[PDB]
Image (cartoon, coloured by chain):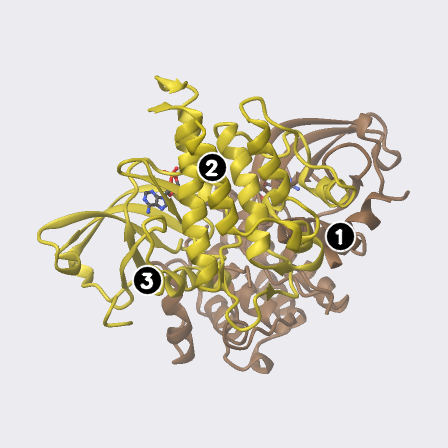
Chain colours: A brown, B yellow
Amino acid sequence: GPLSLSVDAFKIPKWEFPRKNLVLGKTLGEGEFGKVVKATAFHLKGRAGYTTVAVKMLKENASPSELRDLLSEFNVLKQVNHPHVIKLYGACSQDGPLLLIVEYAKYGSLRGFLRESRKRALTMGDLISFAWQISQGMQYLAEMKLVHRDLAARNILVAEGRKMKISDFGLSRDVGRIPVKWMAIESLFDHIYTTQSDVWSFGVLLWEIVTLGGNPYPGIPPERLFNLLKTGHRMERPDNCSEEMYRLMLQCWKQEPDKRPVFADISKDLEKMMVKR
Amino acid sequence: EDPKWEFPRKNLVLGKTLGEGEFGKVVKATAFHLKGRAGYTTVAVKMLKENASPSELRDLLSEFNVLKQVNHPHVIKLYGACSQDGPLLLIVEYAKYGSLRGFLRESRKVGPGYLRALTMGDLISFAWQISQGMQYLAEMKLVHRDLAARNILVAEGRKMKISDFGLSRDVYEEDSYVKRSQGRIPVKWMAIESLFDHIYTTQSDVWSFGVLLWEIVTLGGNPYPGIPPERLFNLLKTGHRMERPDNCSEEMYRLMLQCWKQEPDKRPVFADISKDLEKMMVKR
Ligand SMILES: Nc1ncnc2c1ncn2[C@@H]1O[C@H](CO)[C@H]2OP(=O)(O)O[C@H]21
Ligand SMILES: Nc1ncnc2c1ncn2[C@@H]1O[C@H](CO)[C@H]2OP(=O)(O)O[C@H]21
């Protein structure tokens, strides 16, 4: 079937990394499809010495859909190069478990980074910078006709110099398992995913950023969200949030996808906020 | 919201989290005046986590929709649901010893151990009880799809209860369940035609049952030990199967191998598996 074909293709030069040059280290955690460990890679992509990397691999009780997701992440990330998308360095397909080798983000997920922060100390300026960097990577992805589908603060990584890196491409599709609370209303009711449903998820992410890692729709069971959204309910303006920022969020959550901003409009708005402040 | 099943939310009290399964979290609970039974009754409750996806909601509903229709001494009992004024909750029979995998693994450290005292006779009994439940489920035109020692529970009296119906599917129309998309059952318990061809039948449940048999005789051992799941595509197609474990008779191993025949029609059906296990029991 489709997976057995992808597996066999994968196991049969630009991306293949010698397994002997990879030294696995500390476990960082478990993602959408497997487990992530810190590692050092000797002579990665013509670089001197050891480069610190993150390595993705499957758990032993992996399902076909988890393996499909790993190979999907590899196949998407090969096509991508942007400062605010996590970089793929390669894969080990010839020696034991399949491994993907990716750029290491030393601060971990944006969500943890924020939850450990107070308003390190972060200013609204920082937060808008973070949002803009993500919106740039998203513009780039949308231009390439890739729909991410799983945009969330848990899926953005914070690299050296607090640079945002869009991560976790297991669910992305070259134009469901996405948590209900980050999904666009048409994705919930019609199962459609487009750049405009990525814009919806981006609005939930903005809300996460502004609340420094809050949990969306708190006290609302995801099973009860479908009906609340269809009748027009949205999250209220959070505590330390401007009218303009909240206007931006709300527009991401317009019922009609055509009435949502595009990522260029989202980037424009944050560039304007930055300079005017 | 079915009147034969809906239970007053105020009569249910949730306790500690027992773990997370295929679609959600399971919590120990107590229910007051449950199905005419006086006082409180200890139960297990299935619910969604806060970051639940549509597939996990759909799996919870699938478990409900299956358990509504089945009743067997070796299938976990559904007692009710709360589906109004809050999170959706399934209320099910509590199994005091937890999963079979856990119970067997504890038997390696907790005396009297494998000779809480377990013989091969007890293991055969456990496998037989599960085979009886599966024979009935197969009669009901259901495929479980996720048969594994982690999805069998051990209730009072060490009685086996087939559990975790989130991935179970109806085959009443065509005697097979087929999905275009990729499955969510761990690769190592999947039949070869489920893995390559996406086909699930009672005979792919038989294959999984054979993996469960191997788990049982190894006292909760890990299938295809040391083998990365992606290697199973090649490994199975080229005819390799797990080796006879140390604790296993020739007869018991022949049954496992019959469960893993490449041709599904060459595998035993659950009625015949139950018979093989009965024969083993009686001859000591
Ligand atoms: N490229 C990466 N660099 C550093 N950490 C990562 C990377 N990709 C994922 N992680 C971490 O793995 C976990 C599951 O996704 C999650 O927990 P974390 O440490 O907050 O950052 C993530
Ligand atoms: N009906 C039940 N009674 C008792 N424990 C249960 C029940 N259903 C599931 N579990 C337990 O929930 C956990 C995640 O699946 C897992 O850990 P365990 O205690 O080994 O048994 C399972």
Crowdedness of circle 1 by 10 Å Cα count: few (<14), some, many (20+)?
Answer: some
Residue B284, x across and y down, in percent: 43, 27
Q: Locate residue B237 relative to residue B212 in the image: left or right.
A: right
Residue B113, x across and y down, in percent: 39, 19
Which chain is disc 1 placed on? A
Q: Secondary structure at mark 2?
A: helix
* Of callouts 2 and 3, the N-terminal one: 3
Q: Nearer the viewer, mark 2 or mark 3?
A: 2
Q: Nearer the viewer, mark 2 or mark 1?
A: 2
What residue would you read off at disc 3? B88
Nearest the camera: B215 or A96? B215
Image-quarter location of ligand 1: top right
Which residue is pictured at 37% across the width and 62% down the height? B64
Question: Are labels 1 and 3 on one chain?
Answer: no
What residue would you read off at disc 1? A4
Crowdedness of circle 2 by 10 Å Cα count: few (<14), some, many (20+)?
Answer: few
Q: Are marks 1 and 3 in contact (CB under 8 Å)?
A: no
Vertical comparison of B126 with A126: above or below: above
Question: Are labels 2 and 1 on one chain?
Answer: no
Residue B66, x across and y down, in percent: 40, 63
What is the residue that sits farthest to the left in this orientation? B38
Which residue is pictured at 44% across the width and 65% down the height? A242
Q: Quadrant of residue B250?
A: top right
Residue A169, x across and y down, in percent: 67, 54
Distance CA(mark 1)–CA(mark 3) = 37 Å
What residue would you read off at disc 2? B279
Which chain is disc 2 placed on? B
Distance CA(mark 2)–CA(mark 3) = 44 Å
